[PDB]
Image (tube, helix red, strand yellow):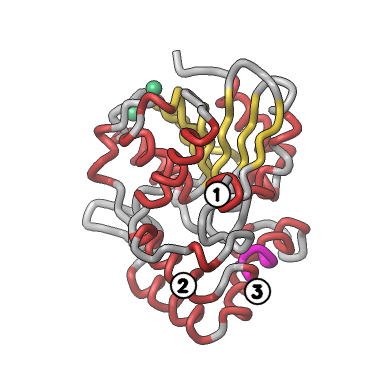
């Protein structure tokens, strides 16, 4: 099937409920490697790659469809409908948290809960808003991608991953970052970094679990509180004593149990 092939959809596990795992920018479904073994005995698990990931065909990257995050939300809904999944627990890493939120606004019937990892509705600082970046910071990041994509990946991956600069996770993310076609990485990086999901948070009706590393290059802790305060749904926050934007990959021993607690248990 076109949908399953385009997004490298993999369906594994067995159980009454279905968990769908959505990855962030610069990585792919392999980011879930340490989580999947803890899910397969109890749940059906769906893994897929975002269009534009290095593992996807650059010829299918539709610039108009992906000019807003809603294009990725429609792909996620297309995957659920293709597999006849009527309800899932959705775990969204980084940009996928907002993709999940937008998909739940279009189709709240398809989601019983959203577990967010490293989420942000806005990265740029605003009047009464700390996002973590000034426009100048992003401008330098985009110029580095234009100037030398290979050197930008090598320098960015250790900062995004956090921890020891020579870890397996740093090596894995450097590799998936550099597998992206340079012009798509720039295009997508700009669309994400320039997004603003703040206005729609009060209309969310699916319960949200907001998880993040206490030290995350792109997500100040205050963003977790901003999401909790503005999401119109029931929500819970858990700030994890970890370093890194992909903590499920880089510190699984301390992070995986937190993610499992929010997948396995519901907000009272
Ligand atoms: Cl629902
Ligand atoms: Na809330």
Q: Which numbered disc covers residue 2?
A: 1
Asked if residue 137 is positioned above or below residue 28 in the image, the reply reads below
Query: Which percent across, then down, holds residue 49?
Result: 58, 50
Which is nearer the eye, 67 or 251? Answer: 67
Q: Which numbered disc covers residue 186?
A: 2
Total count of labels: 3
Query: Which residue is located at x 63 percent, y 58 percent?
Result: 161
Q: Does 188 sit left or right of 178 as displayed?
A: left
Which is nearer the eye, 116 or 236? Answer: 116
Q: Look at the image and give the residue range highlighted in magenta.
A: 174-178
Residue 127 placement: quadrant: bottom left
Mark 3 and mark 1 in contact (Cβ < 8 Å)? no
Q: Is residue 175 magenta?
A: yes
Front: mark 2 or 1 = 1
- As drawn, which residue projects farthest toward the bottom? 147
Query: Which residue is located at x 31 percent, y 35 percent?
Result: 105
Q: CA distance from mark 1 to mark 3?
A: 34 Å
Residue marked by disc 3: 154
Query: Which residue is located at x 40 percent, y 59 percent?
Result: 192
Q: Is residue 215 visible?
A: no
Label 3 lies in ligand 2 vicinity (Cβ under 8 Å): no
Of marks 1 and 3, which one's residue comes earlier in the chain? Answer: 1
Q: Secondary structure at mark 1?
A: helix
Query: Which percent across, then down, holds residue 144?
Result: 50, 81
Query: Which percent across, then down, holds residue 34?
Result: 73, 40
Q: Which numbered disc covers residue 129?
A: none
């Amino acid at each position: 099937g076109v949908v399953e092939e385009a997004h490298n959809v993999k369906v594994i596990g067995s159980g009454e409920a279905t968990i769908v795992l959505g990855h962030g920018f610069g990585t792919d479904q392999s980011v879930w490697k340490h989580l999947v073994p803890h899910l397969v005995d109890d749940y059906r698990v769906v893994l897929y790659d975002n269009m534009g990931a290095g593992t996807t065909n650059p010829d299918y990257f539709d610039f108009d469809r992906y000019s807003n995050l809603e294009g990725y939300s429609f792909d996620l809904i297309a995957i659920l409908e293709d597999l006849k999944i009527e309800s899932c627990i959705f775990v969204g890493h980084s940009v996928s948290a907002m993709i999940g939120v937008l998909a739940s606004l279009n189709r709240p019937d398809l989601f019983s809960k959203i577990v967010m990892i490293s989420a942000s509705p806005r990265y740029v600082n605003d009047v009464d808003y700390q996002g973590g970046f000034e426009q100048e910071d992003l401008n330098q990041l985009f110029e580095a991608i234009r100037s030398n994509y290979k050197a930008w990946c090598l320098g960015f991956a250790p900062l995004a991953v956090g921890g020891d600069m020579d870890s397996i996770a740093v090596q894995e993310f450097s590799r998936t970052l550099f597998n992206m076609r340079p012009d798509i990485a720039l295009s997508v990086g700009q669309t994400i970094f320039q997004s603003d999901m703040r206005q729609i948070l009060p209309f969310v009706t699916v319960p949200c679990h907001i998880l993040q590393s206490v030290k995350d290059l792109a997500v100040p802790v205050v963003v977790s509180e901003y999401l909790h305060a503005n999401l119109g749904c029931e929500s819970v926050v858990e700030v994890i004593p970890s370093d890194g934007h992909l903590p499920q990959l880089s510190s699984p021993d301390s992070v995986i149990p937190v993610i499992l607690r929010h997948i396995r248990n519901d907000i009272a």
